[PDB]
Image 1 (cartoon, each protein chain N blue to C red):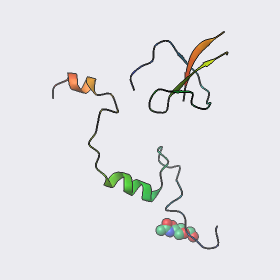
Image 2 (image 1 turned 90 degrees about the vertical axis):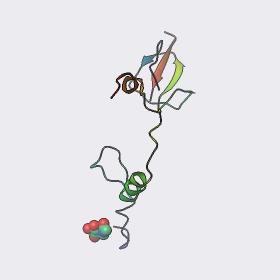
Image 3 (image 1 turned 135 degrees about the vertical axis):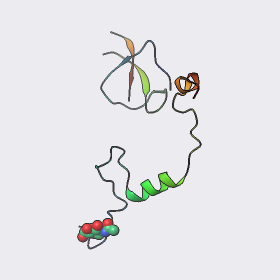
Amino acid sequence: AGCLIGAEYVNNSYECDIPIGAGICASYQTQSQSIIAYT
Amino acid sequence: YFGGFNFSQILPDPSKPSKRSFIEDLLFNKVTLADAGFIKQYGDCLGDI
Ligand SMILES: *[C@@H]1O[C@H](CO)[C@@H](O)[C@H](O)[C@H]1NC(C)=O
């Protein structure tokens, strides 16, 4: 759905918090406080 | 083995990467999509062909 700027992609899988696009979600996780993107 | 019942056309097969069954493959091939911009298309739209 375009490209994301400001969130680091991780190789994990949790429940969807903030929906972005085709199967990608974003969340605010502790592992320093930062925004991550995941499937 | 499920008592003789044949579920091989509705259960998925790992041969194809999009793990869909035979009936699902027929249903997905039958409906001709309009090819909307749910995939990015501006690189195609830039090159006039
Ligand atoms: C029915 O089951 C057999 C296995 O006993 C399988 O070889 C066959 O392909 C199945 N039928 C269809 C149409 O897939």
